[PDB]
Image (cartoon, coloured by chain):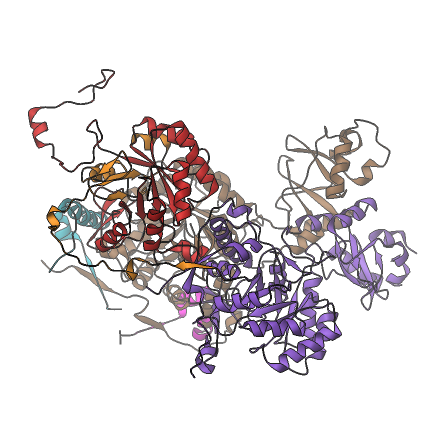
Chain colours: A purple, B brown, C cyan, D red, E orange
Amino acid sequence: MLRIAKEALTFDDVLLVPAHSTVLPNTADLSTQLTKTIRLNIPMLSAAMDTVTEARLAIALAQEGGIGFIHKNMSIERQAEEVRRVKKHESAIVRDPVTVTPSTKIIELLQMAREYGFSGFPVVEQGELVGIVTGRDLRVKPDTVAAIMTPKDKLVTAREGTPLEEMKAKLYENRIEKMLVVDENFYLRGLVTFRDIEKAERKPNACKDEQGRLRVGAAVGAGAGNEERVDALVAAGVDVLLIDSSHGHSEGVLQRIRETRAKYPDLQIIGGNVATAAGARALAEAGCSAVKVGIGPGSCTTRIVTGVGVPQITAVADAVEALEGTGIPVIADGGIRFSGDIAKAIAAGASAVMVGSMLAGTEESPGEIELYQGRSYKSYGRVAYKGRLKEIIHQQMGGLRSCMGLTGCGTIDELRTKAEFVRISGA
Amino acid sequence: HMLRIAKEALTFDDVLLVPAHSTVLPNTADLSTQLTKTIRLNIPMLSAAMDTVTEARLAIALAQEGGIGFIHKNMSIERQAEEVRRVKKHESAIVRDPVTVTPSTKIIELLQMAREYGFSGFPVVEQGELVGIVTGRDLRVKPNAGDTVAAIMTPKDKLVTAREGTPLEEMKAKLYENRIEKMLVVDENFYLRGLVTFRDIEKAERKPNACKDEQGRLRVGAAVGAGAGNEERVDALVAAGVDVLLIDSSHGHSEGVLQRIRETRAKYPDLQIIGGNVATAAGARALAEAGCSAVKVGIGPGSICTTRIVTGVGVPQITAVADAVEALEGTGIPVIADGGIRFSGDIAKAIAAGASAVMVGSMLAGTEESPGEIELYQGRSYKSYGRVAYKGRLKEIIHQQMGGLRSCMGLTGCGTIDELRTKAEFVRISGA
Amino acid sequence: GRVAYKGRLKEIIHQQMGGLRSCMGLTGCGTIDELRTKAEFVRISGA
Amino acid sequence: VVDENFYLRGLVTFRDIEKAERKPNACKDEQGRLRVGAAVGAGAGNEERVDALVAAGVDVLLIDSSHGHSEGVLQRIRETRAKYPDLQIIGGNVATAAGARALAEAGCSAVKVGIGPGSCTTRIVTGVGVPQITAVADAVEALEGTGIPVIADGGIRFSGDIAKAIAAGASAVMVGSMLAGTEESPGEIELYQGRSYKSY
Amino acid sequence: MLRIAKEALTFDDVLLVPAHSTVLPNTADLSTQLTKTIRLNIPMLSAAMDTVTEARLAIALAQEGGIGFIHKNMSIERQAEE
């Protein structure tokens, strides 16, 4: 009769305690296991929201050390292509060069030579690379390009995914200043020079897989009928799959995860959302590589409409305590205002945090930049323009680094286990 | 004895333009106009010599849209003269800091470099003077120990180069016909200045409305004070190649301002000179005879601007521009409207009042190209140096304002700027 | 019943006569009697 | 009036001595001179600044950082106490019993308390802080035998908060924004919108 | 797991209790040891802030019974001279 389980605490009810510290903020280590097999370089994920994460933003976040989740409010064919866009992103490769076909008339070949120079036009037949035709090819003679082009068997090419230093070596050792880039089927994918490799921005903190590719996630619904979407994302090379619903403790959610884990025994899977120790055990039992926590975590509409929610400090600690033996990490999702809340979510036991509205309106998130009343927006009903995602990550991990300097926790894992709280009041 | 009221004076809010029969499509309206007798703009816009608005980056961005920007004077003479040179020399098709060797460079260091930068061609420079180049073709013969590049390089006389300022199509002609992949850019004294390729010329964003001088160079302006002691500044700006000099003060009908202008016209007979600010027919005529090529109008234009509140002085702007234009009729000295411009509608009213162009300041602060660098602060983007709202690229704002000006010229049937200045009419409206 | 402290009277005089001096340079009235007799007005609207 | 090197420093008459304002409550040293403090950073490279302040006759030296429990802060204090065994030293800021013991152990003559003490930006950005009544009582309780006093720094709005900081065990309070804008603080008096300011 | 050290109180969470008093406010003694060797006549120090304490303010506070702290946002030679 009147069944109060316990008291639950939110971010604003606690503060972290300063401790003896030998940690400089700038020497603090921000890396963390997202799953047993995936390690992030900063403890941050972007939400699968149509105003936050598509391929552009997911690329920019992976380059800073985290992982973005492509939202599902798009066709299967388009979402899988957003995942491929992140997996195959290399800044040094020039895409869409000017090409010809083996049927191109020499007179056309000369009209373009005067417009683009005669260094070498790739010859393609339906996207398959078949050769290159240079000025030497024409001015020494044998009508159509096929009769004069340098053939496939004398081409010096690199495969997509070749490291920049290997590509520089190939260019040097074959004495070439252009090198065409092909896929496994010898389809042209771009080209590289020494100069394009040089101005490729270097990203030392990028979260990359064992092949050196940026890591990416994608979201699917927990409903039935998503099997075609899941198989397309896995086949696209997604690193981690997000099965998200508003009630992760639902039995049809637990069943959908069990079925994906049986089909892909090695696929890294995140499920949510839960807010109880029992909800987290149930998701780990279904086969999750990680557990996302957040059902009405802060002063939200699920609470107003349904009556339901657990304040976020308690939700994260209960889930972390339910999972303690398993090497299955907890993600704190929702309610993250300032960098102080990131530090508190982690000290409560979370291994990473997911953020959403904080990143909408950045340069890389979806939407067009719009000028309206002399002030900058991203429009698609508009959100403030917040500049580059790089600067916001800098501001938020600065504050986390300061928190670790203050609590004497030099790594995320120490913050999660060693840092302490005091309980404070409203006034 | 008698309250000396010279006349009634009208502001922008007091009048509306009358729509006319029109064969003008807004997107076919001709926006070009004369700034002085010798300088033609492609859009009727200038950026103010404010330290929060105009330095070299914004002045380039604006010349590339068809206007001119004025480098503010709140920096050293050497800095302001460098800002002017940056605009006149700007061509994004030229790669600017290439890796060079010297005749003294060992072949071994050269091979080390060729592994990092390729062998397309290292410029050989001694003291800044271009003296040769070394490509991977020039090397073929096994080097001995301690060999220098001077042995194998291509000499100066066998080089194909192009002078800075050469039209980009001429450089393409030269790259193609000489069968070269890159070409070195030099200056009057054969000092190495950069290089071009077919790809760098392609990648440069095209700007058909760029406002350029008869040598193809972007135009630029610069401001100085009217006080004594700005002689050296003016000489340094002229020497930098500035296209027009702005001698600015808060009272351009002041005798010391007029004197400074006579002295600059005396020293620089062909220099294009803008003077301001004035708000009467007599101030404008006085500045014409001192030697101005154009006249800038605007004395306490806004309702609550500080000059009006502190000094009581001002003339509402519509009357002040009509007053000055009528003074200058038949002189080919254009009038510029400075200050009080809120919307794109205020631009069209200044021109139909007779002005040949308008000057804007704070509308452009906080753009990407304006000074300051971007700061995120409380979920919003600003430019910090006290912070102004980040407004995006200058091109978007120009587009929006000229879109509102084009829409007016279709409404009034004025297909050119001179038609608007002479043909379009007004209705006087009340405050209700 | 309390009014804002405004500092020394000299500072306020300075500021107001600075604004009056700026006007006499604008209108070219070098004395007060020149301003009283020579300077002119424009009639403006409420807009 | 001359100094020790017979350099002229001023003069006095009967009238100037008479109109010298009398200040019965002045905090003065054993020589009758006003007492003063000076602040230095807790970082490395401040040894030239410290030696110049001590040589200037500073009465008490303030070694202040945002994390007084930092190990490089504790080490910097240990090094100053070895060099000037008699110099009065204040270190901060801490907010725990352990932080205060560590500062007293390093050689502090007094301990300044205040890490995010009231509803402040260290709390918002880092997540860290201890409310100020608890911070002061814990430090005072950690120092109870030592004759090393506690200063309550930060969060002091009204005179009621001064009384509460002291009842919690603090021996003095430090205040800042309460005194900016006074006649004597830095800055020039400025009239702006008929209202008086100190501007910089 | 979820490590709450304790509850912590702020100025607004407590009030002082009135007690039996033989103290007149104007006869209350405000002096206090700042260190074992330094005694203040009022329990107040001014902060080492560039907008608060330089020599002028530090002189005016010492004359009232406390001690001011010259801020360090200035050259060594200037701070020692303050």
Q: Which residue lies most toward the right here? A: A142
Foreground residue among B188 and D3: D3
In this rendering, position of residue A24 left or right of residue D81: right
In this rendering, position of residue B95 left or right of residue A9: right
Q: Quadrant of the C terminus of chain A?
A: bottom left
Evaluate whether residue B334 shows in this view.
no
In this rendering, position of residue B427 left or right of residue C31: right
Please state the horizontal and vertical placement of residue B166, each as a whole percent of the image: 64, 47
Foreground residue among B234 and B383: B383
Position above or below: D45 against B329: above
Is residue B420 covered in magenta? yes
Q: How many marks?
A: 0
Is residue B377 covered in magenta? no
Q: Residue at x 33, y 62 (%)?
A: B322
Foreground residue among A260 and C20: A260
The magenta segment is: B408-432
Q: Quadrant of residue A48?
A: bottom right
Please state the horizontal and vertical placement of residue A411, each as a whole percent of the image: 57, 52
Position above or below: A278 against D118: below
